[PDB]
Structures are given as structure tokens and as C-alpha cells.
Length: 230
Length: 230
Ligand SMILES: Cc1cc2nc3c(=O)[nH]c(=O)nc-3n(C[C@H](O)[C@H](O)[C@H](O)COP(=O)(O)OP(=O)(O)OC[C@H]3O[C@@H](n4cnc5c(N)ncnc54)[C@H](O)[C@@H]3O)c2cc1C
Ligand SMILES: Cc1cc2nc3c(=O)[nH]c(=O)nc-3n(C[C@H](O)[C@H](O)[C@H](O)COP(=O)(O)OP(=O)(O)OC[C@H]3O[C@@H](n4cnc5c(N)ncnc54)[C@H](O)[C@@H]3O)c2cc1C
Ligand SMILES: CC1=CC(=O)c2ccccc2C1=O
Ligand SMILES: CC1=CC(=O)c2ccccc2C1=O
Ligand SMILES: [Zn+2]
Ligand SMILES: [Zn+2]
Image 1 (cartoon, rainbow over the protein chains, first blue to last red):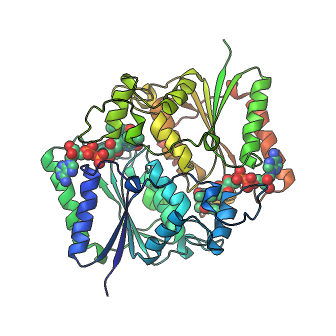
Image 2: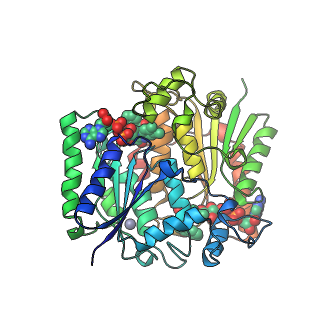
Image 3: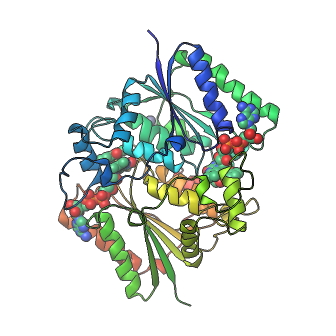
């Protein structure tokens, strides 16, 4: 049996370092004989806003709209917006979910944040109780491929931007692990725009190279200690 | 003389605890005689996507689209989308910027993330010469008024969600401090949905009451130590 992979891609320019790191993952994983699917959010013009338009049935409480309550109900009633369910299908079948994106304000670009806000709804990605170790999407793997504007030094404990693991907390722990995902070590391609053509090629190569043995990797200890190191 | 406050509001329902917190802020601040403006993102159906549409006119390089470069150029060129500039006019005139939003995946809702991604562009919010303590928007105050689903205990250093100061890093340090803002201690109305009518009123009341002396408040030492250290 093989593996299914979903690459949530968030970048406007196809000729970008992000586009390349995505094409690379597709080429490599496909070469391995893996089933690959890519969600080019910008190309799809994915709706980032969480509104009442995400529910197609009668609202539970039309007087006071509570997005969480409504989407949770909609998911169970199979009345969620189509674009939401489409992504949920790809995630449900995936064994590995890779997020390819440029660092936007120490987090993910708005279009990607919307993906996470609307797709990973209650009932699908988690329950109460049913998060973190017992998240509904448990068993699946997750990996963040982030390119940055700042350099590696900038992202050290004593660096101006602080340790890179600090901003990974919301994404890796608060989102991914919360949904049950097993987080693999993030892939951070530091300051490509500053790097030389050769250094860039090295970063792209390093990605492909790592992917060759991606299925043999063990997930990181998604704990507060891993991110902050007390 | 006088004070200007911009409240970037991010919530779908006017009858929500978030709507109430925003309304109260408008009340107290207006009572104080302050100049108050509110950006109801959802009502405005604000565009969270950072696309080429954000630039009006000829792109500096239409062959390869680089958002940060295109926008920075468009800012200096006065070729940015009106919806972005409008928000920039408000921010530039404000003395205090309050963000009212529910916690979405240890961060801000996608619509709000978009506001931060598109409005706080290079040339306006920051620039190679100035960031963090030398950020372009230096001198201005900033405050995050966030409501959470999880209780306070869940947000302790030894809790499931970890210390609240952890998820605040990317927002307070990575975004606000990066632009030069003076970050005031955040206001976190923990699990309002779970709280009793009595407890909630206490949360709302604490919000307005705090607003009475906001101008006498000292900006928190936005350091890594503050967020993670002891
Ligand atoms: C809204 C916003 C917020 C931001 N927030 C942050 C932040 O919080 N922290 C931070 O550090 N940075 C930040 N930045 C910067 C952002 O992280 C970088 O712009 C981004 O990571 C760069 O990646 P890119 O794909 O856009 O690269 P590109 O601009 O495409 O640069 C890559 C270069 O490599 C070339 N190239 C493409 N493919 C290949 C290939 N296969 N081999 C060799 N060369 C190739 C490209 O053509 C180009 O010359 C922000 C920028 C914006 C617009
Ligand atoms: C995509 C998504 C991601 C999420 N991620 C997180 C996360 O990372 N962490 C986390 O902890 N939670 C998370 N949540 C939950 C979210 O943080 C909470 O649902 C939200 O903060 C609750 O705030 P609210 O304004 O919607 O409250 P409401 O649902 O409006 O509840 C307030 C209650 O008080 C009533 N009320 C209204 N006005 C007043 C008033 N003036 N005085 C008294 N009572 C009043 C309301 O009608 C209601 O009964 C997430 C939810 C979603 C949809
Ligand atoms: C927040 C931020 C930090 C960077 O180091 C950086 C470097 C180069 C371009 C943009 C950015 C940016 O927006
Ligand atoms: C991450 C997260 C944590 C909560 O405590 C919570 C509570 C109620 C609804 C949703 C959430 C949520 O998404
Ligand atoms: Zn974790
Ligand atoms: Zn800071």
C-alpha cells in the first residue's frame, strides 16, 4: 500500500521559492509512487472569511450567530459549504499534510489561516473532549514548510526575532497537534531572497533530499519544552 | 491635544460577547471625549487575501509577482488599493489601536490576519531601517482584546493550552512591536460562553473600568522573557 499526501500551498507567484519547494515535493513524492494532491489556495481563490455562508441549512440559533456552534452542527448535518467539505475530503484521506507557505507576521498568510479556521471545524478535526493527543485527525502526520524573510541568526534565542520555534507554537501545538496530527520537524528555508542562487538551490535540494526519507521520520515532541526550552 | 482610538473589530454577530466588548469600548472612550473609529471587518467584508489586486497600476515587475515588493512600491507610489489605504489613514491618525477578536487557533481570525497582512505593509508599518523599537508606527499604543473558548486554568504554563503569553508572541512581538507599537497588557476574557451571566458582566465591566485609566497605563516590556521567562 502507498501513502496519500495533501500539500496546502499558499503563494501567489508560481515562479517563487515557495512554488519551487512545492513543485519539488510533488515531483519527489510522485516519484516515490505516492498519491499527491495540492491545494493552491490563491489559484482556487479560497475563502478565508468565516461567515454564515459556510452553512447551507437552517441555523441552529439564527438569533445569535455563533460560527463554532453553527459549523459543528452543519458538519454533522452535512450542511457545510462545498469548498469546506472538499478540503476535508483531501485531509481525511491524506496520510501526510504539508503546508507550503511564506512566513507572514510570524504566522501563516491570511488565506491559509482561513483554510485552517474553516476546514478544521469541530466534529471533523476535533471534539470536546477529543483534541491534542485524542484529536480526531490522530494518526496523520503534519509538516510545515516555511520560507522566511529574516536570516537564521535573526531566529535564535538571542536573535532580534527570537527562536524560530517560538512562532511555531500556535501552528504546531495550537492547531495541528490540537487536531490529533503528529508533527514532523518543520522545514524552514531561511531568507531565500537574501541567499545566493547556489544557497537557494541548496535549500531546494535539502527539501527534496529530506523527502526521500520522510516516511521513516519520527514526530517531534510537541511540548512547551520543545518550543521554549526551559 | 485629545486622543484618537481605532478599534479593529472582528466578529460576525453584534449580540456576541465580542460585540458587547466593542460597544462598551466605544461607550467609555466616547464618554471620555475621545475620537473613536471602528473597523467592523466582517461588516466591511474586508479582503484578507494578499493578491496583486492590492496594487493599482503597473506592477514593478509583472513577470514575477512579489507581494512585499509590489506593496512597498505601491505604498510609496500611492498605488495601493483604497480599502488598504483607508485603514492606513485610520491607523496613522490613531493614538490607540484596539483589536477585538475571539481566539481562532491560538491566533486572530483569518479576516483580521488579512488586515495585518495587507494594511501593515512595508513603507507604512515598517522598513529595512526601522522595525521593532524603531518601527514606523512607533509611539502609538496597541492592545489585544481577545476572548477565548478555553478557561484560564487551561492557559497556564502547566495547562493543556499552555501559558497565554505563548500564543501572544507572534501578535504582540512579531506584529505590533515589529511595527513600533507600544503594547499594553492584553485583555483576555476567558471562556465567556462557559461563564455565568454574572461572571460575564464582570468581564465586560472590568473592560470598561480598565478603559477609564488606559491612558495612564505603562506599555509591557515586550521581550521574549516576558512571554516565556520568569
Ligand atoms: C505580509 C508579509 C509578512 C511577512 N512576514 C515576515 C515575518 O513575519 N518574518 C519573516 O522572516 N519574513 C516575513 N516576510 C517575508 C516573507 O517571509 C518572505 O518574503 C518569503 O518567505 C520569501 O519567500 P518567497 O517564496 O516569496 O521567495 P522569493 O521572493 O520568490 O525569493 C526567492 C528567490 O529565489 C528564486 N527562486 C525561485 N525558485 C527557485 C529555485 N527552485 N531555485 C533557485 N532559486 C529559485 C526566485 O525567483 C527569487 O530570486 C513577510 C512578507 C510579507 C509580504
Ligand atoms: C475557528 C475557531 C477556532 C477557535 N480557536 C480557539 C482557540 O484557539 N482557543 C480557544 O480557547 N478557543 C477557540 N475557539 C473558540 C473561540 O475563541 C470562542 O468561541 C470565542 O472567544 C467566544 O467568544 P464570542 O464573542 O463568540 O462569545 P459568545 O458565543 O457570543 O458568548 C457570549 C455569551 O454571552 C452572551 N452575551 C452577549 N452579550 C453579553 C453581554 N454584554 N454581557 C453578558 N453576556 C452577553 C452571548 O449571547 C452568549 O450567551 C475557536 C473557535 C473557532 C470558530
Ligand atoms: C516581520 C518581518 C521580519 C523580517 O525579518 C523581514 C525581512 C524581510 C522582509 C520582511 C520581513 C518582515 O516582514
Ligand atoms: C483550540 C480550541 C481550544 C478550546 O479550548 C476550544 C473550546 C471551545 C471551542 C473551540 C475550542 C478550540 O478550537
Ligand atoms: Zn503540541
Ligand atoms: Zn516586543
